Length: 160
Length: 14
Image: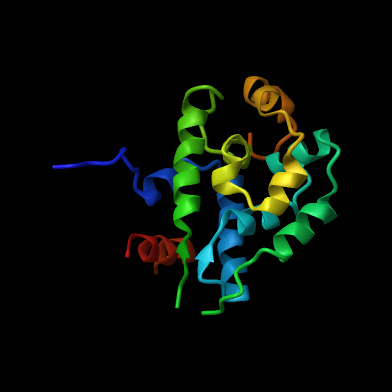
């Protein structure tokens, strides 16, 4: 009978998270609940990682000359308009964690899943994962450099 | 007992 590409269960992926990456995911989830959104999204995670200057996501934006305020406003205006019970992760966020773990465990040479790999996978498939506002903000970030020099570019990170 | 992320993960399966 017909099968699709293998999917890893969410709790196995969450267990790969670096301890600080995981703490920020827990913050993203609380944020979602506080806002009464229906799904935890990559935007909620970004929103919280932006508050730590040594997150991988901050370190990438600093290197790209991007301002925290512009990314915050793009996120504020694309949050779900629905108000809701515990949310689920969005199916796009589950699938994103699985691609970012596959990249981490292979090309990035990372023992743990970090927000930098999650961000790199979303940027590498930005048509799939990024809203039009984020695409346009992040258009100039060099994915190949970030992939090839991941560990050095993000050497200052709290997620190491 | 179940954490926030535990509850959210269960909802994700369901």
